[PDB]
Length: 460
Ligand SMILES: Cn1nccc1C(=O)NCc1cccs1
Image 1 (cartoon, helix red, strand yellow):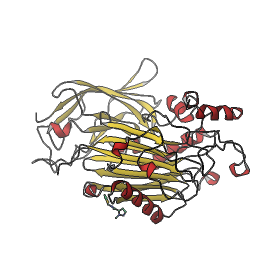
Image 2 (spheres, protein in one colour):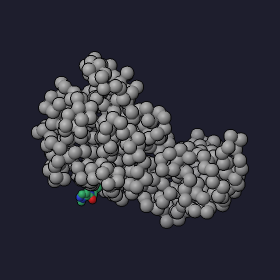
Image 3 (cartoon, helix red, strand yellow):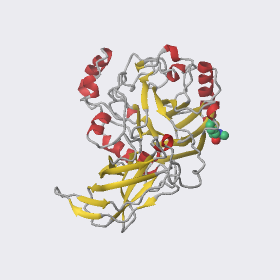
Image 4 (tube, protein in one colour):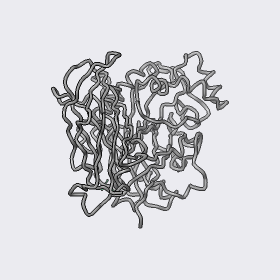
């Protein structure tokens, strides 16, 4: 039975509004309703992995698992295995997988982050799951961010705290946050970004939604605007939104948006908004294709509609050779030529690099680079041809060209990372000097760039 080179992943996010679900929720797992929907001809084909994020979830873990497994069994006639379940307050993540994947999945991690301080600590935050699927690392984050149209900057702060403090994936990747630890990272939830239009325009917005004319509303969506201005979710993708706003509905119908201020809302307006979102970030040149992104029309117990997204994702096999694992393959080498980091920092410490990759036995520390002043006020750290030659565990090009090198640039004085990035080994040529590039981030904000040339030797 051959190992897959592709899997499909279902991501669901639903703010349940503290109410039990209706008896039938299969439309969610089938990607049916509004937006980019799944073809009827696929309905019996199970996804490989189902990741369900809930917010304001009133069920026990047992109660929800029973509903989820019974839903998937009805659709697919497959009894899914539970990979992980993790709940913080009323924020929950469930990962289910086809039974045939049980002995492909390992290194399962769970964690949560509580956002806010005092007043604002006690209900918002994020839960996450990571694991290995054969050679491929997968991370999943379900966040419920701060509510309210006038709190976009709080949501951005919540995002930065979650990506700093959520402890998933390989703890040896110590310079790297969750935005660099995974081949594929899916981040979803009630992100709570709103359509930023005046309150007086509520009925106009409703009109537009009835006409399925979303363009003038999406141009005011806070998440799209904040992402365009590089304030949040830097280097993440989101499929185009072609479904109606998923909040705030009157319960038991989808015919009415309930936007007006009420005691129950703290006298806040809730103009129709795309609160409920799925974003992802995959390593460079890895196959990832969104095949659905939409909302259900027939699940009406909450003031939010459920959102679905499905993905094709490239995966690799757990490679063994006669040499690695447990030794180097001397027919393999990675040389970084004429590399330099450009940093936004005002500091004047010396810097060194760390190269991290599961194609190495352990991470590699470089010598300190040579600091120069850049023309427009920046720091340029030059590494020349000084960088250590990297010795991969396996030389086979079928393995090595699918790998990635994570780079951290660290201060000699503090050993703290000033920037993290990633280089694909999916090159146009081997034994050939080829340009490489990554942006560098720290705490998920842009701090610089790393560019140079690479020369990759494989056994072929
Ligand atoms: C026993 N258990 N309860 C909850 C989660 C688990 C678990 O560790 N499952 C391992 C699997 C890998 C793939 C399918 S199942």
